[PDB]
Image (cartoon, rainbow, N blue to C red):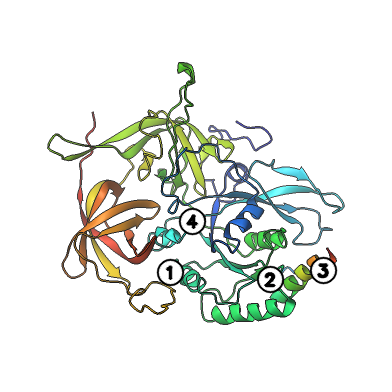
Amino acid sequence: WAGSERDYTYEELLNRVFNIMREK
Amino acid sequence: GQPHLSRQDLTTLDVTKLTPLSHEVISRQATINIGTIGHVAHGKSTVVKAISGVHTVRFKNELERNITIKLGYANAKIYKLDDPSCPRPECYRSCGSSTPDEFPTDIPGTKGNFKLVRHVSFVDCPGHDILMATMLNGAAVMDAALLLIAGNESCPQPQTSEHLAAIEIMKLKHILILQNKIDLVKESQAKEQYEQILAFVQGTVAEGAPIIPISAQLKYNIEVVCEYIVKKIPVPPRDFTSEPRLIVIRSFDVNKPGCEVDDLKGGVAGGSILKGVLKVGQEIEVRPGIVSKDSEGKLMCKPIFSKIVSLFAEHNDLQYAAPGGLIGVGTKIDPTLCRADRMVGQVLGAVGALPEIFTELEISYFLLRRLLGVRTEGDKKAAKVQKLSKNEVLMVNIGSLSTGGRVSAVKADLGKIVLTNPVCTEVGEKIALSRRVEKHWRLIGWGQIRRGVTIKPTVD
């Protein structure tokens, strides 16, 4: 979604996972 | 020797040019080691299974010996998608070691063929033998770590402190944290667990490490783990120029019962390569080889000289083997000497390029006094480490070379250890010690080989 060539944060990965089980 | 993989030619091979990122070596065998410091029932095995698929093991014995000590390995190929349209980390994908170097995209990422990037090996042990396996010798056991914390429990669980103490003692600078089993965890619960995790790792080596949340069972955010393996994990330095050395971990007799004479094969010895490159057809010496006793009962060792018939890396066949995984050397040794893991604890290397054979060691041990990262619940003396005593059997772990030892004398801090079997080592090597606390072997200190009794290897 963005140019995250740098290390992420815990929040984005956590909400990614949560999107994963909420959509399926 | 296997299609759809990069060709390996001994003639077109140079040791100096070899690097851990060489495409020819990575195409067939893993080059870097990433030990997973987790715990059973928390997804320690499930994470590795999801990352590296399911293995089959080319050779397996009918009886497994030292299953609680064996250093298991698992190879996984990580690839990157060259199409910039596909967003990260979906471009990074993990798969097995038998896949071809390039396969077409299986996702609607608007074309783009995947290309092999790296080949990793997961050093997983059912316990904590990793600690004294790699804690002072260093060698090239691994250069990364995968600290695993589950999500159902609350950090810090009583099984977490030992993991952090292990991460600290291993002197590992590259650690990635994977929060497993967070699928059945509320967002607030996950946030507070992450806060507890960062509080626990505050002021420790895991300060600047990812806290990536993944679900091993459903294979969620594994691509993030692959991405951080690519980027966060640096390329380790390896020495491909010295004479090859391999610590033998496994040993198989591949001849099935009732086989023809022409179908007989030699002894396949699995192991780990420390420094150097092994070549097919190279003369090799295994030490201490055949260990026997005289009529009066005097130890004698005859090193076994043989030739490398073939090399295997999981299901792949190699022409030259490099450090960074479990390599199985199929040789010309008689299957009698290599059946049912009977050659474990021996060093296999170039002829005349092996350390000395020791029967007794004189070490300068520093004894630990409490088990690393253990909660002393009720019994205060349970976690206490008693001083070394005479006629006590420890577990000397010189790198990946495991051997028993009976303490014969202690003066002030110089302890003499009488090994059960002679082992190949050199004076001044860093060794570790373990003691059977209960149902397990636990690290209790380390030391240096000041002196030692050596045995002259008879050769006929």
Which residue type carries mark 3? Arg
The numbered disc on residue A7 is 2
The numbered disc on residue B125 is 4
Q: Nearer the viewer, residue B50 or A24?
A: A24
Which residue type carries mark 1? Ile
Residue topped by disc 3? A22
Q: Position of residue B174 (x, y in %)?
A: 55, 66
Q: CA distance from mark 3 to mark 2?
A: 25 Å
**Callout in the foreground (4, 2):** 4
Q: CA distance from mark 4 to mark 2?
A: 29 Å
* Chain letter behind tag 4: B
Dot 4: what SS? loop
Q: Rate crowding at label 3 as few (under 14), some (14 to 19) or many (20 or more) other CA atoms within 10 Å.
A: few
Instruction: Answer left or right for B85 relative to B423.
Output: right
Q: Are marks 3 and 4 in contact (CB under 8 Å)?
A: no
Q: Nearer the viewer, residue B425 or B13?
A: B425
Q: Nearer the viewer, residue B43 or B315?
A: B43
Q: Is residue B235 visible?
A: yes
Instruction: Answer left or right for B456 relative to B55.
Output: left
Question: Quarter of the image containing the N terminus of chain B?
Answer: top right
Single out the residue that lies furthest toward the front: B378
Q: CA distance from mark 3 to mark 4?
A: 35 Å
Residue topped by disc 1? B169
Which residue type carries mark 4? Cys
Q: Position of residue B328 (x, y in %)?
A: 48, 39
**Corner quadrant of residue B428:** bottom left
Q: How many numbered marks appear?
A: 4
Badge 3 or badge 2: first in the primary sequence: 2
Q: Rate crowding at label 2 as few (under 14), some (14 to 19) or many (20 or more) other CA atoms within 10 Å.
A: few
